[PDB]
Amino acid sequence: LHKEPATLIKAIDGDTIKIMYKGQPMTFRLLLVDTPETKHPKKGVEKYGPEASAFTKKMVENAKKIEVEFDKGQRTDKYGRGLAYIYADGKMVNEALVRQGLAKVAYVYKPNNTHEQHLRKSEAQAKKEKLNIWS
View 1 (tube, rainbow, N blue to C red):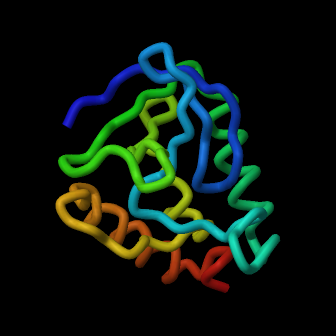
View 2 (view 1 turned 90 degrees about the vertical axis):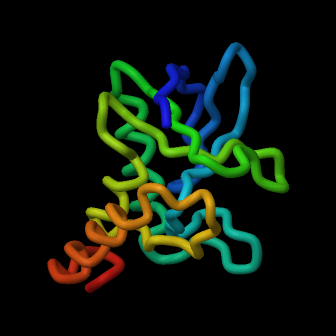
């Protein structure tokens, strides 16, 4: 797995960010994490939804460099969204959200599950600290 440079275009939700990748605007979905949504299909603006959303947004908007890291499996989902680990200044956005109890580790689909263990380790820590979602 390789990190590739990308440019922020706009944060959309806790789990979705629009980025310029290899010169193309693309919507990216954060791999392996589910955050509460402000959009969400059925639901709507669930609890911690606005919180996860502001977290992702501040973190990617205040970064000097954003990098995209594809997993070993398919790289887009059925909506055309990129499936990646997103890094802000060397820090993985997907892990940061899980470490703060602002996301749960998702339904996992091999072979896109390389950082599954790391994330689960951060999820257990946030639960144990009883943070946000976990309180």
